[PDB]
Image 1 (cartoon, rainbow, N blue to C red):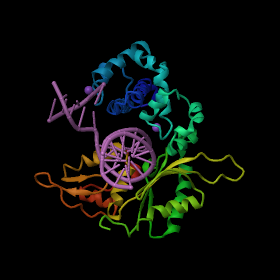
Image 2 (cartoon, rainbow, N blue to C red):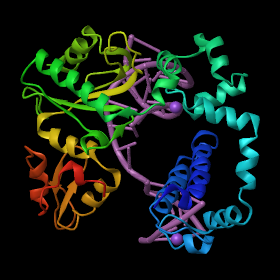
Image 3 (cartoon, rainbow, N blue to C red):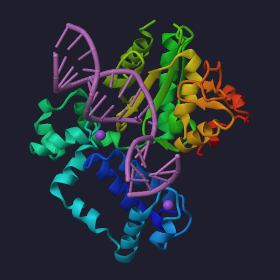
Image 4 (cartoon, rainbow, N blue to C red):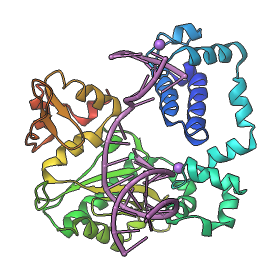
Length: 327
DNA sequence: CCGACGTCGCATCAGC
DNA sequence: GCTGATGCGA
DNA sequence: GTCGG
Ligand code: NA
Ligand code: NA
């Protein structure tokens, strides 16, 4: 399916999806619209009617009508009106700043703050996270070429081992699935001296080293188990400098690492197929563990997992490369 | 007819 | 000062 | 908004 097929409809739905989350604060309607956008995007036929589309899982009466209106006119009256609404479009925009959610974006537009300009005129009203998001508003909306991700992974794997060679680190996300680009970098971290049944400076020291070699530039949030911050490659001598990137590092217990690795590798749809799979075989998988039920449906103690493949074995199915994990 | 729709670590703030 | 709901991101 | 119990 090419974009030109039903891309006109998906954009309509994606726009509608954003206004639900950001303006109406109806997060479940937001996911509903996105779900429809996805299933339509995979649909290898130029849709001729709302009735044709309503056949698909995720699309019902109300969306079918909108598709009819779009097909008949080329536009949607409601979306047109809300694109042009000064309050709503401003609220919707401000949320594109990382750190600004639909709630904060509400109060800003309430007291008159609508634009990035206005945000810069009033930074003492922004918190630490929001200032970073504002500062790198453009960079964050860029994607990362796999080549840069590789160079980023190069730096991360090196400085981690340099801190302590017993560390294990794995860059997951769409990147591990061989994607040609990424939106950020998700690093999963563990150590033999960290288990579910067991220092509380393991995460700090990795972050510390990456700040020393000037790879990590800012910090959105940092606790004992998860780091959310900003990073940047060394500018290639005389050349044009790199965009700042979003990077997440989280520390996972050794006996939950590969379950964490499996989970955050994805994809989303792959993961649902594999956890619904799965119940049929009599196991429950979350991001942390895999547990056995249980004739009445009562889970037992989480089975030991020492590799990704280990999990596949439990549920009787031949190991899959991250490459082939899109569904 | 009406509830589920993913979940949770960290920063911030409301209540006390 | 402490407890913990809410906002936010993923 | 969609699905389904
Ligand atoms: Na349907
Ligand atoms: Na945001």
